[PDB]
Length: 142
Length: 139
Image (cartoon, rainbow over all chains, first blue to last red; front, top):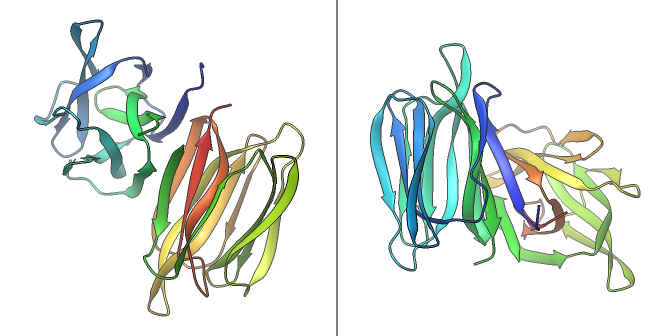
């Protein structure tokens, strides 16, 4: 709606769908992983208030990406894996205009990659259960 | 503008179609790999055709009807004759999925478009289609 562009999601059809939308300013992403991607915390600001939304389960070790001023997310990549009979994100990583992060997780499968030649990630959607079943992104220019 | 990709290798020469008002058809030329593509589209009242990559292989045309648009692109980045090129390519419209075009396996990629459409292409081409990316537009 309102001219949104959404790409993905990559992963399985399990869990419950989530959709953050594109209205917020992402300040940090915390990927929780072990054998696979367990979940993600997305911290954002909106009208001067900071909020964190958690998607996926409670397992894994955290791996944070904190966006500096003038830093934005410009790439996402990972692996869609079969794990415990579920189709989930086995690995997940991101790139900013400053650095590459991860990928986090240890289970390979079907790779996906989102290099963004022009534009940036402005929000998330996907599916979460015990693990992070799937992830997709909203895009906007610059 | 929103440009995602390109997926593929660093060989050949860069190409950039820019965005179209409407894509009419995409013709994928393939054999062992993806040799190239023809894109026919409307642009500021004009109908235009552009060719990217080589002209080997056999053409496979996808014609987009009224109200039909491209909502996905997927493929495999393959190693072929000492080059890294598109080994397979496919597209999905809001009506049906098409492909694969090409026969060489490699590293898969996929671009499902949950909201929006492909409006144009960019990438690299030589004798084959070295790399391909897309311009995205909202619905």
